[PDB]
Image: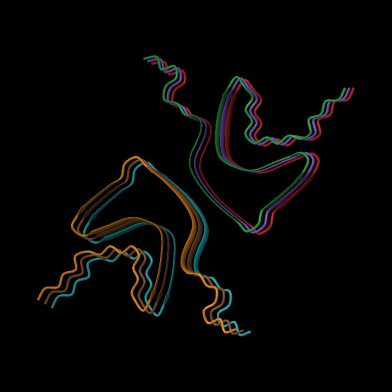
Chain colours: A cyan, B brown, C orange, D green, E purple, F red
Amino acid sequence: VLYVGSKTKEGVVHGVATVAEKTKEQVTNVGGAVVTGVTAVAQKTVEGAGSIAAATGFVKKDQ
Amino acid sequence: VLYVGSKTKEGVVHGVATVAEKTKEQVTNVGGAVVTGVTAVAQKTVEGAGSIAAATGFVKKDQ
Amino acid sequence: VLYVGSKTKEGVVHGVATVAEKTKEQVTNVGGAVVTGVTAVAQKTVEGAGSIAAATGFVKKDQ
Amino acid sequence: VLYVGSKTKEGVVHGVATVAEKTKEQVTNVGGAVVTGVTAVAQKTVEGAGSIAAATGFVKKDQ
Amino acid sequence: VLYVGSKTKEGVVHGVATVAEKTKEQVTNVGGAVVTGVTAVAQKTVEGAGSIAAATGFVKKDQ
Amino acid sequence: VLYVGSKTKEGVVHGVATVAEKTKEQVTNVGGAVVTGVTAVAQKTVEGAGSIAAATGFVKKDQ
C-alpha cells in the first residue's frame, strides 16, 4: 500500500439546489465582453491556466 | 498495491437541482462576446489551458 | 496490483434535474459571438486547450 | 362580464426539480400502513374528504 | 365586470428545487402508521376535511 | 368592477430551495404513528378541518 493518489476529491461541486424567479432580465453589449449566470461549474487543470468566468476586453497589439 | 491513481473524483459535478422561471429574457449583442446561462459543467485538462465560460473581446494585431 | 489508473471519475456530470419556464426569450446578434444555455456538459482533454462555452470576438490580423 | 369563475389556479403544482441519490432504502412493514415518497401531487375535491398521503392503522369494529 | 372569482391562486406550490443524498434510509413498522417523505403537494377541498400527511393509529370501537 | 375575489394568493408556497445530506436515517415504529419529512406543502379548505402533518395515536372507544 503506497496510495500515492488515494480516494480524493478535487475540483468538485455536489448537492446544489437553486431557484431563480425573474420576471425580466436583459443584457445589452456593445463591444467588450459580458459573462452572466454561471452556476455549478467544476474544473481541474494540470500545467495550464484555468479560467472559469473571465470576461476580458479589447486585446489590441499595434506596431 | 501501489494505487498511483486510486478511486478519485476530479472535475466532477453531481446532484444539482435547478428551477428557473423567467417571463422575459433578452440578449442584445453588437460586436464583442456574450456568454450566459452555463450550469452543471465539468472539465479536466492535462497540459492545456482550460476555460469554462470565457468571453473575450476584439483580439486585434495590426502591423 | 499496481492500479496506475484505478476506478476514477474525472470530467463527469451526473444527477442533474432542471426546469426552465420562459414565456419569451430573444437573442439578437450583430457581429461577434453569443453563447447561451449550456447545461450538463463534460469534457476531458489530454495535451490540448479545452474550452467549454467560450465566446470570442473579431480575431483580426492585418499586415 | 360576470367572471364568476375567471382565470384561477387551485390545487396546482408546477416547476419542481428534484434529485434523490440513495445507495440503500428499505421499508419493512408487519401490519398497519406505510406511505413513503410522495412528490409533486395535486388534488381538488368538491363536497368530499380529500387525503393525500394518509396512512391509517387497524380499523376494528367489534360487537 | 363583477369578477366574483377573478385571477386567484389557492392551494398552489411552484418553484421548488430539492436535493436529497442519503446513503442509507430504513423504515420499520409493526402496526400503526408511518408517513415519510412528502414534498411539493397541493390540495384544495370544498366542504370536506382535507388531510395531507396524517398518520393515525389503531382506530378501535368495541361494544 | 366589484372584484369580490380579485387577484389573491392564499395557501401558497413558492420559491423553496432545499438540500439534505444524511448518511443514515432510520424510523422504528411499534404502534401509534410517525410523520416525518414534510416539505413544500400547501392546502386550502372551505368548511372543513384541515390537518397537514398530524400524527395521532390509538383512538379507542370501548363500551
Q: Residue at x 57, y 31 (%)?
A: E43
Q: Is residue B17 above or below residue F31?
A: below
**Residue C13 x/y as whole percent:** 47, 62
**Residue E35 x/y as whole percent:** 69, 41
Q: Nearer the viewer, residue C31 or C47?
A: C47
**Residue A16 x/y as whole percent:** 51, 56
Is B61 situated left or right of C41 in this image? left
Which of the 4 image quadrants contains residue D1?
top left
Which of the 4 image quadrants contains residue C1?
bottom right
Q: Is residue A5 above or below residue D25?
A: below
Q: Nearer the viewer, residue F48 or C3?
A: C3
Q: How many numbered dots are placed on residues in this image?
A: 0
Is E38 situated left or right of F58 in this image? left
Q: Residue at x 38, y 72 (%)?
A: A50
Q: Nearer the viewer, residue B35 or D54?
A: D54
Is F42 situated left or right of F34 in this image? left
User: In which quadrant will I find the C terminus of chain D?
Assistant: top right
Q: Is residue E60 above or below residue B50?
A: above
Q: Residue at x 21, y 60 (%)?
A: C32
Is D58 situated left or right of B5 in this image? right
**Residue F51 x/y as whole percent:** 66, 31
